[PDB]
Length: 349
Ligand SMILES: CSC[C@H]1O[C@@H](n2cnc3c(N)ncnc32)[C@H](O)[C@@H]1O
Image 1 (cartoon, rainbow, N blue to C red):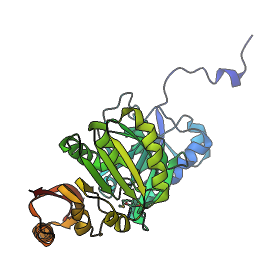
Image 2 (cartoon, rainbow, N blue to C red):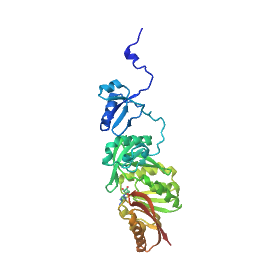
Image 3 (cartoon, rainbow, N blue to C red):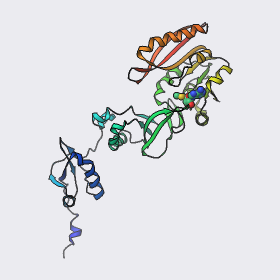
């Protein structure tokens, strides 16, 4: 006998060759419509010109029932392989250029998205997921708030969580970005100072957070590191991090829950002080006062202020009756015309 038409109609083996032609101002509306109705063809790319977009569809009869103009076109096939290296490869320049730098913490991607391009959130998320297929959370960042410098963060894709375990320089760092400050970009600096350190040193790190600096130093050197942190949630994670890394640390770490400006005057002095100073805070006198051989003092300085910065460090050295060599390094581009810097102070005997 013969077959039912509603069985035969699925048998055609060829590929779809049609799309719908829509005004650009209608493109987002129509893309949503095509997906909801279920006739968007994932096999092919959409294309555009100056005025119109063409979406690939799987059923032109249904497209007509949606009031859409059907066109016969030769659209590109979806890519089977990927060779994108960076975000710029996946976004138009007008969008990418407005994006802040992207940071990865554990399996969380963090990016700043100005209100002006927030309307492009979908393609931004798509681009980030493509570039980082292992990321499980994407968050939009604002500024740091409060004494603990917690970053304003909104999850815009993935799991609704801001805690993860970050890997750096051979150590494991538990972080909860909803509760503590963390600085992934300091990876190079932390490794640098860890290599400079010598076995046997006693080292102080004020403003220590979940103690990434003490962990990286103690990973590579048999030293004792005192860490001072005021945020009790950061202290908790620091304790958990110490236990998490305990069997891989050569050195020892002492975590002190407290206010740096209260704690340091009551401490003994140290061979080396490493101060990842909160932006805007001046802890130069106090941290130098605890150093016997080396201070590494981080700060944020406008380029035109860079020389004044060095002379202020030298002034404090003389003020404390110390003879020092001071070297200033640009550590990172913080924003236009402003650098994160480090004063390396060598105290001479
Ligand atoms: C950018 S701030 C870096 C870390 O220093 C901590 N911090 C800020 N001020 C102090 C202080 N006075 N004493 C101890 N830790 C501090 C913050 O909670 C954060 O974890």
